Image (cartoon, rainbow, N blue to C red; front, side):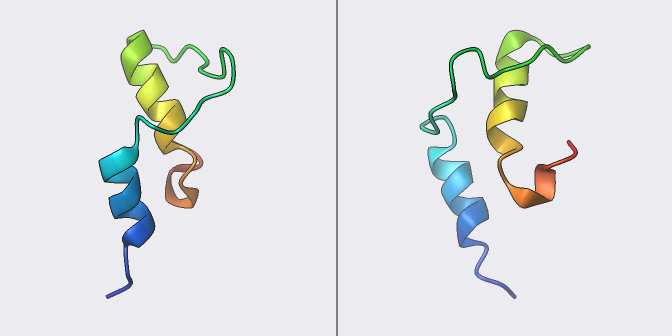
Length: 50
C-alpha cells in the first residue's frame, strides 16, 4: 500500500489549509460550508475534477 500520508494529513488538518480571499466558488446543491470543503479538498490531485 502507498503511504497515504497526504490523504491522512488532509483528513487531520484539512480546515487549516489557507484559502485565497473568496477562493470558494458557488456549487449548486452545496451550502457555503460544503463548497469550502470541496474547494479545500480539491487541492489533492485525486479530487481535481471533483
